[PDB]
Image (cartoon, rainbow, N blue to C red):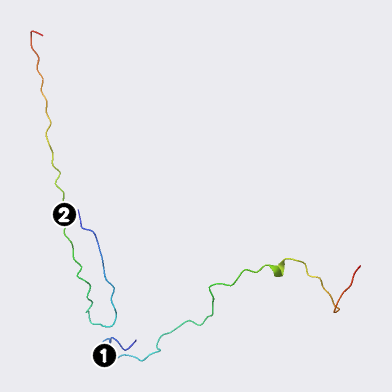
């Protein structure tokens, strides 16, 4: 509500409250496989070796 | 010895004007304690013949 109680007479409509422009989140996950093993760079579609 | 303090209520917020319904802020009762004191005593005597 915002119409209750009138202090003392004059009151305003809904949506008169300032808020905070930013975005946040409580958690993410755990992540580890993307920074463990080495990368092997390869130009071609496939590679062979003996 | 003062009383304990204190259980205070929360204002429901649909009214205004003081108008505030605070349960009465009762000042309890100031109290004391009587420190009673007793007497202890003893006697003894002797004789010339002992």
1 and 2 marks in contact (CB < 8 Å): no
Determine which quarter of the picture holds residue B6: bottom left
Q: Is residue A14 left or right of residue B38?
A: right
Q: Tell me, yes or no, whether dots 1 and 2 are on the same chain.
A: no
Please state, as top left, top right, bottom left or bottom right, where the C terminus of chain A lies in the image: bottom right
Task: Single out the residue that lies furthest toward the left.
Answer: B48
Picture coordinates of residue A48, whole percent (x, y):
89, 72
Instruction: Please give the name of the residue rendered at 70% of the width and 68% of the height, measured from the top-left corner.
Output: A33
Picture coordinates of residue A8, whole percent (x, y):
25, 87
Q: Chain of mark 1?
A: A
Instruction: Please give the name of the residue rendered at 18% of the width and 61% of the height, measured from the top-left corner.
Output: B28
Determine which quarter of the picture holds residue B23: bottom left
Please, is residue A25 above or below residue B3 in the view? below
In the picture of the structure, the residue carrying the numbered disc 1 is: A9
Instruction: Please give the name of the residue rendered at 45% of the width and 83% of the height, measured from the top-left corner.
Output: A19
Please, is residue B3 above or below residue A50 in the view? above
Q: Is residue A46 left or right of residue B13?
A: right
Instruction: Please give the name of the residue rendered at 84% of the width and 75% of the height, measured from the top-left corner.
Output: A42
Marks 1 and 2, how far apart at CA:
47 Å
Q: Secondary structure beneath disc 1?
A: loop
In the picture of the structure, the residue carrying the numbered disc 2 is: B31
């Amino acid at each position: 509500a915002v119409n209750q109680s009138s202090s003392v007479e004059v009151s305003s409509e809904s949506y008169e409250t300032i808020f905070s422009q930013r975005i946040i989140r409580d958690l993410q996950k755990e992540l580890v496989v993307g920074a463990l093993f080495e990368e092997l760079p390869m130009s071609s579609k496939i590679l062979t070796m003996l | 010895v003062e009383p304990d303090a204190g259980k205070a209520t929360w204002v429901a917020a649909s009214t205004y004007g003081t108008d505030t319904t605070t349960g009465e802020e009762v000042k309890g009762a100031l109290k004391e304690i009587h420190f009673s004191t007793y007497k202890l005593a003893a006697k003894s005597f002797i004789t010339d013949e002992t």
